[PDB]
Image (cartoon, rainbow, N blue to C red):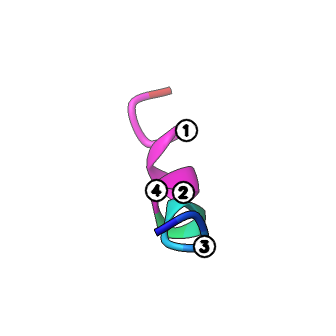
Amino acid sequence: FAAAXGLAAPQXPAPF
């Protein structure tokens, strides 16, 4: 799960 966060990282700047 924690590691999965890595994939959500690229989504952080997605909307930005």
The amino acid type, in three-letter code, at marker 2 is Pro
Taking depth in this image into account, of 2 and 14 the one nearest to the observer is 2
Depth-wise, is mark 3 or mark 2 nearer the camera?
Answer: 3
Question: Do residues under tags 3 and 1 come within 8 Å of each other at their CB atoms?
Answer: no
Dot in front, 3 or 4: 3
Q: Residues within 10 Å of mark 3 (few under 14, many from 20)?
A: few
Kindly indicate whether the residue at mark 1 contacts the one at mark 4 (C-beta within 8 angstroms): no
**Mark 2 and mark 1 residues within 8 Å of each other at the beta carbon:** yes
Amino acid, disc 4: Ala
User: Is residue 1 depicted above or below 14 in this figure?
Assistant: below
Going 44% across and 49% down the picture, which residue do you hit? 11
The range drawn in magenta is 8-15
Name the secondary structure under disc 1: loop
- Which amino acid type is marked by label 3? Ala
Q: Disc 2 and disc 4: Cα gap in Å? A: 6 Å
Q: Which residue is mark 2?
A: 10
Which numbered marker is on residue 8?
4
Secondary structure state at the residue bearing disc 3:
loop
